[PDB]
Image (cartoon, rainbow, N blue to C red; front, side, top):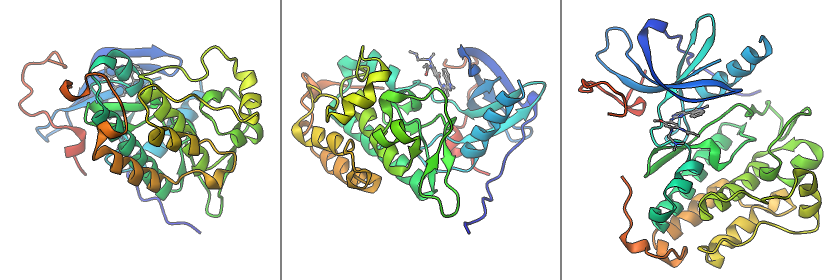
Length: 310
Ligand SMILES: C=CC(=O)Nc1cc(Nc2nccc(-c3cn(C)c4ccccc34)n2)c(OC)cc1N(C)CCN(C)C
């Protein structure tokens, strides 16, 4: 069939980590900024802790399953889970937040080199997920986090599906889905593949190149499947040369097999990242620059999760 998934699921002691401040609260629960100090190791690891219904527990454990099974510099990984009266996911702290919020807040100091590098990094992350036979199903700028302005990672595996041994697609049930990011065949037939992820990657790039605009703003999601069928697509962002826009457009072909592969998106955006001002036209580009967080003073032993292995 397929290879055995030998990922380790680490179970953490609640006394080993300290919540410092709330980062966000919603129906997903409450995310805290915090520190994880595994007993006896003399490391302090900055973490986000997602604290949390018996079906809502089955949902967060599926996410933990997926996150524990990935290991790539451009994908967020799970440090572990804690099974208290509520279930908590402990993941790497990504101090600059979501890329969608980052491009909105810093539109005036984001140059072409950052934008094209992020495109490369997300393609690398998605290519890795495809190698792992994983379909994300919710790729979007809100679901990419910023570790540093130079380093982003794909996150939010709440919808992700490992495709079975001989499965090329996944057929979902019904529910609330992110219509404005989805391939046409996913909207119409609830079918999802690596190539429908390519479609959402195209939409994600469009979000970045417009510094966080909302795709198909105002148009109700009811009408999206019809608009796409007529052959309409998102418009060329002002900063985009035709080279970059043609890549996005190719991600939105009706024939899924004629969309680019993630490994080709890596190559094409890497070429453009070598001469970024040739491919994105940003006023003031050549002079832009981008870069306590825990209210604790003795951070001598702090270690990023990426340097904390086994
Ligand atoms: C959309 C809001 C957002 O991303 N906020 C955010 C996030 C982090 N870091 C972080 N690192 C890893 C995971 C998460 C995270 C995961 N989930 C599910 C979240 C839900 C809401 C907010 C944050 C998260 N968050 C963070 O680390 C210091 C700070 C912030 N904000 C307070 C700063 C960004 N703000 C301008 C929106």
